[PDB]
Image (cartoon, rainbow, N blue to C red; front, side, top):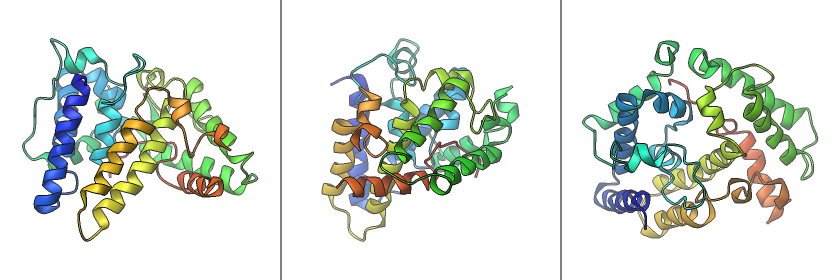
Length: 268
């Protein structure tokens, strides 16, 4: 449908293949494209590499969709601009692989001070997880766990990081490039997608037998329910306006309790 859609469909057909042929190697074409894209900005646009590095996921399938956003047709707030991806100086999806899993893991090793040369995500990413632990304890153990209270508290934590770049009033967590790229509850939209796609991907890979029906449901989720056209109204588990309902609240408690809550990338 678009150049963004073309690469995704090719990767999805390649993933459906590798799963059938030999269960791939975790994510196989998603890993190649994630690393291909992740080596391109590192070599060619270090400011955009710095902007999105704290947001990359160890699940390369999740990283692929959070970076490309191939089904986003509404808005011009792509995480990485269309010019950098498909323009005359664009990536256009050309493979930049060799030792792909080695290359992917080495990307997380780059979350350091020297790479930025300062946000706490680059200086002390372990300390950022300490701050998010405090917020997690505050919401789940220091407040009422209600349909009325908990959804509002999750948005407030993302709100503080959005406009003040702080967690527990300690900052700066991210670069300002990263902050302005996550305006209007986009990070909460990213992190619910993390939690949802993580669960279905983990389930897909844990099963004995591969069935294309389950991989299609993951793709159907990213196309029709979380395409990226409108972040706050694509919120489901984390939407306070949405509060079957207690099943939804169950995933909210699990999301806060997960590492996808206020997600930040760390070396290991």
